[PDB]
Image (cartoon, rainbow over all chains, first blue to last red; front, side, top):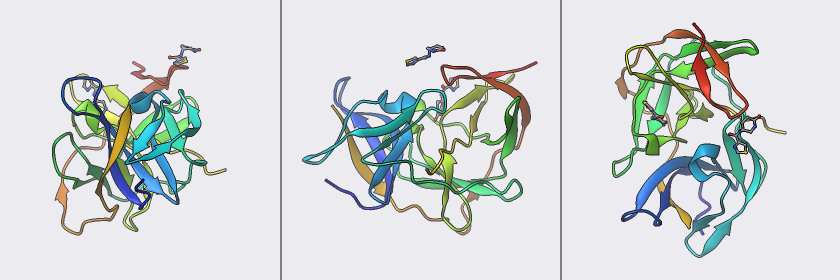
Length: 156
Length: 39
Ligand SMILES: O=C1CC[C@@H](NC(=O)c2cscn2)CN1
Ligand SMILES: O=C1CC[C@@H](NC(=O)c2cscn2)CN1
């Protein structure tokens, strides 16, 4: 199948028509997405098959064909871009200054941008174009708005 | 059967639309991977 680096839509034909359930990143021969997008199921890329390699429900991440490759981190000061890939719409970069999720185990960057659920897995980038995390796991705040964590895995 | 379709290159766009605020929130993360507001 297609193994070229880049952002991909994650589609299903089980429901009505062809529905976009999420998004992911192909880097160094590995496909990276959020666990809630695929639930760990196998993926198809043309005539080829992508099998899960690593996954974790608590981190809400999963990699296919190999170990997690993305290790860039938000520097805690600079603006970033969400490369949003919404269902039925073209890829579009949105620039923002991330906020912060403060937890009992440390602070995590967060992006306050609202997209349909099928946009989960879109990458968040730094100014060098490095993927610092994926968009799509977060919280609904006091005004009905959506705030996603900047979710990053660990490169072993 | 889920399938993937290429949607683009991963590159920073100079002069992209700039939006969104930067809220600082107290949150908890449970074993199911769900975030929640701590208040
Ligand atoms: O990528 C994303 C953006 C939208 C988000 N949707 C919600 O779960 C939700 C429930 S109430 C408001 N948003 C899911 N993940
Ligand atoms: O400790 C816990 C809390 C709830 C449950 N987690 C999941 O949602 C889950 C388990 S397998 C897929 N999702 C099982 N573990």
